[PDB]
Image (tube, rainbow, N blue to C red):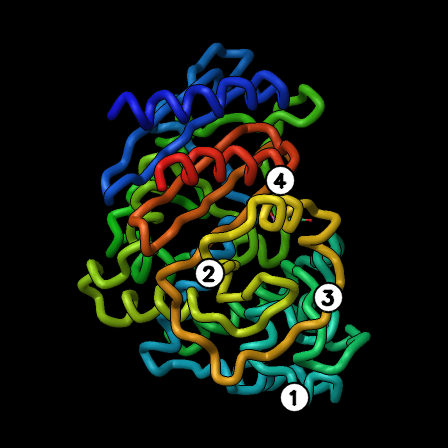
Amino acid sequence: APQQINDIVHRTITPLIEQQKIPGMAVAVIYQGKPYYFTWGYADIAKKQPVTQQTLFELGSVSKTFTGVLGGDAIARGEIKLSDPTTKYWPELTAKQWNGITLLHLATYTAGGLPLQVPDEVKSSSDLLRFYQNWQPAWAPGTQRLYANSSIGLFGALAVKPSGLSFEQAMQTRVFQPLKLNHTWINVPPAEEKNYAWGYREGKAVHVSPGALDAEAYGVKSTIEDMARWVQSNLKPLDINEKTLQQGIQLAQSRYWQTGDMYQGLGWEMLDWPVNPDSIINGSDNKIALAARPVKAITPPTPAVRASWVHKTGATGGFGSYVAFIPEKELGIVMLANKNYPNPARVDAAWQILNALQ
Ligand SMILES: *[B]([O])([O])C1=[C][C]=C(C([O])=O)[C]=[C]1
């Protein structure tokens, strides 16, 4: 890799691993549409397995970007419309609070207060129905944004309903396969377990636990190589031959709502570039990213803006991931660590690296 890129990455990630005590990490910088890899530490401390470009990391909420794109693909295919009411795909959902709550609302966390987490007690299919039937909106739809798994997660499940495929099957056939993301999984097979890093929480090795809507909200695991590929596809959707997928990617980068200087897409969150570091850096901290905020509707949504900082943070008990790209500069970065460390530290490092490359 150009010594230029090598220097900036090393000078930035080395002190980060040191200060955040990250056991293992993999970084991918996409520069001029070409990827460059870097890896540090351990995937498995106990078994002394090093992190490699084949190591699988939990993407956590970065999985939401795949869901947003898969939903975008369904829209492109004419299977669903973001303007359709939620009940069109789940008629069993008869509670009157759902009146006026659309797929757009579920996809963008603006349904009216759906919670961040689906309760642990909610498992069966009838349990989820009851959960949603009983839920009480604190606000009218399309007024307030509250980041939530139960919101975009439901969107993912309903979105693949017409395809007749299971969420996982739809995701593989419609997104992973076409993009050649061959080491990206919702459920990692026995054969790949050897490459699955252990997450570390308070020094204990852990992996994400099963949950309702987990696949749709935070259950994807991937390698630094496949995530580099995921970035390139999102930086250049026109390079994709599958019409509906290409279109799906564009739809996920459209700006539907605005809060502060952030714009909500389907899974991805965007900001006008050049962006102010302190603004995306502090804007990422969970003190802001997860709070209740009023949103302004973008009527109609602004189609994907090439000059934007497109990104998403992701976390699980044991993992911390981050993805950010600038379509206009054919520039991007993927950071995958097996420790959940502060978001601001991720964004800060990401910005130092990309800003230094234009
Ligand atoms: B995501 O990585 O931000 C995310 C947020 C919350 C949860 C949860 O509480 O289970 C999973 C993933």
Element carrying mark 1: loop
Disc 3 target residue: 293
Using the rendered view, name the quadrant where residue 203 is placed.
top right
Element carrying mark 4: helix
At label 4, the amino acid type is: Asn
Disc 4 target residue: 343
Q: Which numbered circle lies on residue 100? A: 1
Q: For the residues marked 1 and 3, what is the alpha-carbon distance in whole angstroms?
A: 20 Å
Q: For the residues marked 2 and 1, what is the alpha-carbon distance in whole angstroms?
A: 23 Å
Element carrying mark 3: strand
Q: Which numbered circle lies on residue 67? A: 2
Mark closer to the observer (1, 3): 3
Q: For the residues marked 2 and 4, what is the alpha-carbon distance in whole angstroms?
A: 21 Å
Q: For the residues marked 4 and 3, what is the alpha-carbon distance in whole angstroms?
A: 19 Å
Please say if the residues under marks 2 and 4 sit with CB atoms less than 8 Å apart.
no
Picture coordinates of residue 357 (x, y %)? 35, 37
At label 2, the amino acid type is: Thr
Picture residue at 60% right of the left edge, 76% below the top: 105
Q: For the residues marked 3 and 2, what is the alpha-carbon distance in whole angstroms?
A: 23 Å
Please say if the residues under marks 4 and 1 sit with CB atoms less than 8 Å apart.
no
Mark closer to the observer (3, 2): 3
- Earlier residue among tags 3 and 2: 2
**Vertical arrangement, residue 260 with respect to residue 75, above or below:** above
